[PDB]
Length: 100
Length: 100
Length: 132
Image 1 (tube, each protein chain N blue to C red):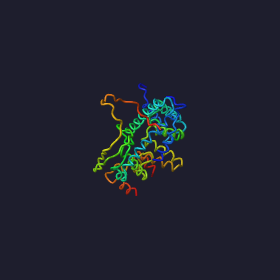
Image 2 (cartoon, chains in turn cyan, orange, purple):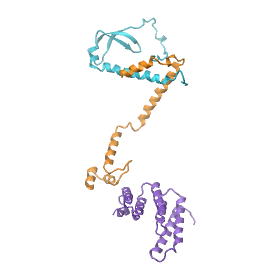
Image 3 (tube, rainbow over the protein chains, first blue to last red):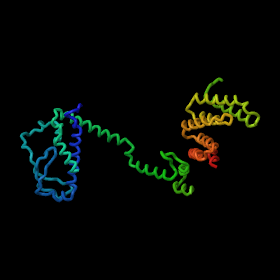
Image 4 (cartoon, rainbow over the protein chains, first blue to last red):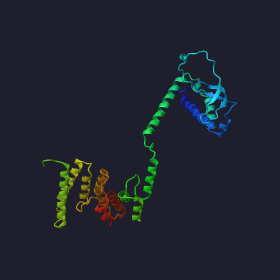
């Protein structure tokens, strides 16, 4: 490619985008790794859920299982009401870049 | 980590690539090249010598040998080394007793 | 005459060296054996140029070059160094440098050369005698 001009910072931006996520994941660990997170995680807690299903959809945890080893969260998460019933319409799309 | 994240977020919210015509293609191609280059780097390390668990202990042993007079710089055996070579047991102590 | 190889050239040079040595050692003459020594050098140099990657030929040239009748010490040092470079496991060449330095009042550096020689071969006689 040719990056002279409007694209000069194209590689460096990428690094800035990636490291934050790595840091965020580490920061995310420094959230669950703490004894205080293990105390806060209970009923009456709202969390932002990030997976393939929910993309930063707001959800509220109803309860945390007493067995704190396999912490499975029964959680109410908002998603679009499904106007379909067939998995065949789902297909791979453009990889969502982390934008500013 | 949080302060570096804050600075990266501040810089990212001013990026010039976000306004470029060719932001997705070049950027994804850079993603691909860096990922492949990184996997190559790890692969080369797996075939190298630093992977060896005991390499630092070998280095420390060579230093202990060279501090006594048994090995020249850059590892060539001296006369004391060849004496402790052809000895049954307690090579270091026995050759030290002999020289003393 | 009938099979021209390097080893025979080197051996012929050493033989001429021995003949000159015997003539001098009986005090029978001096300066009337010059042609014999030049012939020995000619043969040894021919052997070295025929195959210049053999420690033996360089070492033989060095020993002959420093004989009392020739007395060319610079060439001798050059030859011993080349012999050492050709094959690192070489007690003979190191001990020959030790002798060369020791006769020219250089006790320290000769001591170093002898030390290297015995480090490479603990049961070589000349290095131990030089140390004594």
